[PDB]
Amino acid sequence: PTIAHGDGRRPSKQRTFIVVKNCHKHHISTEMELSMLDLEILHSIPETPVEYAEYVGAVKTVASALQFGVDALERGLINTVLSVKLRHAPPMFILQTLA
Amino acid sequence: KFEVLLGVYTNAIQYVRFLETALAVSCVNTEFKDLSRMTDGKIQFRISVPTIAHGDGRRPSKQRTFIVVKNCHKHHISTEMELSMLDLEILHSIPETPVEYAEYVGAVKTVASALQFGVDALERGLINTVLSVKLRHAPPMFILQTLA
Amino acid sequence: MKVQGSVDRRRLQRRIAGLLPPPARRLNISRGSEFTRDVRGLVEEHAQASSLSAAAVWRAGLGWRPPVFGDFLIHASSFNNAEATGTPLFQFKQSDPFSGVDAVFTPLSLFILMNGLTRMANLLYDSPATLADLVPDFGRLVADRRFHNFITPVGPLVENIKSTYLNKITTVVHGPVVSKAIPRSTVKVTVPQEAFVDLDAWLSGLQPCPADARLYVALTYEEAGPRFTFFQSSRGHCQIMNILRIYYSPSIMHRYAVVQPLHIEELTFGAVACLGTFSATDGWRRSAFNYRGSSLPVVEIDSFYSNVSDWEVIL
Amino acid sequence: EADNQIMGPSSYASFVVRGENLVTAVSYGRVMRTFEHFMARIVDSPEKAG
Image 1: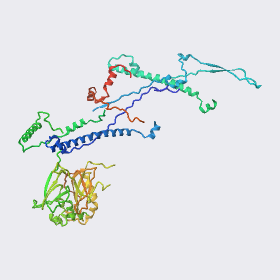
Image 2: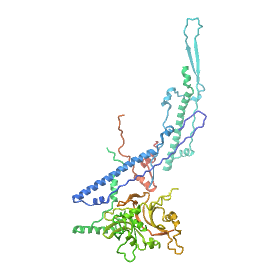
Image 3: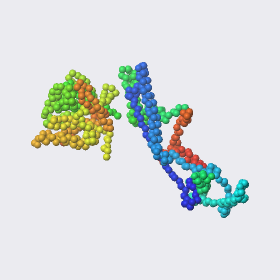
Image 4: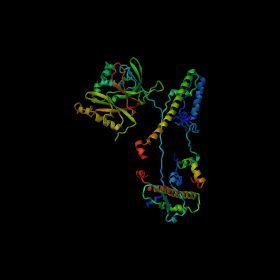
């Protein structure tokens, strides 16, 4: 929008701006290890108390690995959002006068 | 695999009315339907000023009256809008098929907003004119202080 | 009112449970009923893997990489019982009797035969005259320069069953180095740090970095006897030879006197082979031997894929 | 200042590709943001000035 003015100056016709923004995509990767011995017994059914002990040890370690992984992805999310915020933040000494 | 138009936004122009501004405190707003006829205005003050009697032989000042005249000043305000002749053309014809109806409604919306802009520009003109008139008769402070 | 988070564990559990390969089929021979049941499972699996009629009978959806083991038998003098596992070894050919000993050779044994590292090699081998008895024509084959044709590379050793005179030895020939006794525990390969030249730094826009870096082996007849060198490079089989010749030129300049104008059998300066491939962008690791008189620093490299090459002439 | 507490949403705002967008994704390879909105603006009401 414009202002009407009484000076002889020429009036400005109507104007519209069309601006386009586009996305930034971020990629995230982690790793998980599972020992082959730990994987083998999970399929089998334990019968002796020793096999019960080995089965429960395997399930504990596996659950630990999975929980650590999902926490790794949460932390990665927070790091990526913080990097996004920083890369598009100009320094102050510019922006106090640019604003 | 696809690409997505995930957001469409358009700015909204807030109306600005003179009476809602605090600046309007410093004015008196009269609606005068046919202003173009008034050639010249006039206000005439008549003021009577008394004096105090004195015991000295001093020559006395008689009865005092002053006659002050003030006059109107006029202002002209104008803005220019541009309309594409195709829009003003298709506005008249009826719609034949729904694509014609979509184009018709887009056209009438565009021209309506083109006039919204005009009324808004004229309002900003009113308010700027009052502010400039006030600035023209505002002498600076260091002159005003010792004169008051 | 917990947040529930941003990622879901059910998805991960499901997709990983999908990724696990089905278990190997144990067969139980001691008990009759278990044997019968596993045989029933076997016939059902063959019916499930070979019939184009059905679709669930299609199982190929979603590598076999042990090494090729080769066993050699060697005398207990021509090998220290203490020598570390994974050192590349090189083999020699006997003329008539081969079953008695194979006479496989170690780099320190070559340094001894060819005449700090010297003292370590003597503290391994004080009286290495058996070493001279293994090659009768050593003094002949240095001059006939046929020494490289007979020294064939065998690569890293995995296991050595220890006996009084003979030694049982298992050698990685082709493929990645791996063991056998357990679920295939890995090994690494060691070469002494001295008498090893890094030809990627000997000459040191931006040079490109390949995925795989190779180790070559070369044998040179200098006036100070023969000597062996292994080269950690990455560029290409067509450029490593050129760069190596440029390297040896100062040593090549000395051979004008020894060469024979009449008999052309001695002229070759050396030969180059390619042993195997390892991961670049990593480097190698530094360690010393732990023997009685051990003072030699040694480079050791992970991820060795043993792909031995032949000796190629360079001059 | 003795507040040390704010309030925010507990779960993210979900967005899913429905059939009306799925046909456009399959054929034309483009998806619109919440097609329901643009359809309620364009086809259902003639003006519905914003």
